[PDB]
Length: 333
Ligand SMILES: COc1cc(SC)ccc1C(=O)N1CCC(Cc2ccccc2)CC1
Image 1 (cartoon, rainbow, N blue to C red):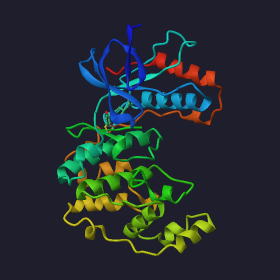
Image 2: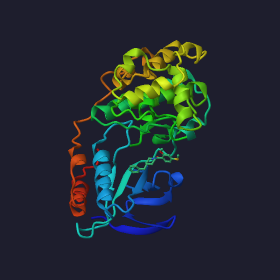
Image 3: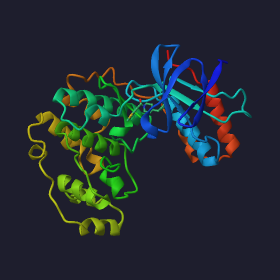
Image 4: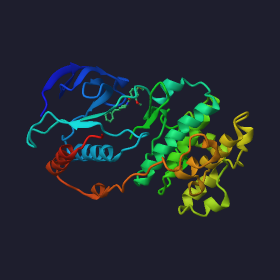
């Protein structure tokens, strides 16, 4: 058990192993209580996150367990995972704080891109990495559901990891409260991000929820007969038929001057019917990514057991399960 020290940052008390030095807050609170630090063991800069009130209630405790389990499972170059997890507690009874450590990327996509058009090569590199991480996440039978620039951790060299208005990147089926959705809700977000990197403009900057849907449907058209046949709710259908009916735009007339392969990929990502939307693995094989695609280096995750989500346990049970996961953590090589 290492020597811990205490430090106060932004009125938060941190107790961390002496391994982690030069703590300084990062993210201005957007990502919770997070500090950058120097990892004396590796010479790398890391982000340390102090979980907030992890065992105050059953919901917090199960959330803590959820977050630790997920981050422990995610082992991929383009997904945030764990370099370390620790607690100053020396026993389960003492256990009341959880710290997580990962590589410090230090910016989100928007801080790196600054709403400029990127070159087509630069867009290929960024979107390729999002899709490579998404293929991994999706292979674990996980859906992100809120992919957007601020959830992409990106360094100055545009190396990117997925972190597991706010509404500009959300799939229409989520906006429309459809009860079933599939992993390609995330591919919708990717398409929105790719469009914005190419054009320098948010694709669907709706003023509010309704406007958002109107901007989406103007580009992708109102639902075709094949999609309408899959909507179980008469009122939802009546709702959809209530809207102004619009044919789909030809994206070649929207993304003027883009690489035709990018437009083609966007067409396959921004399909209204999410059953017809390209998956992450299919997108990685698309000719747009020929310079980056390596089918033998786009790894998938081990099966991820989420059955705890269906359980109703007591606080001390979630806390003990979380302590077990702290104890069993094995750092990456
Ligand atoms: C979008 O990413 C950033 C954005 C910024 S300013 C917009 C600054 C820093 C990062 C950055 O490097 N983060 C990575 C670490 C994240 C917290 C965490 C710690 C440990 C374990 C899991 C998670 C926060 C985000």
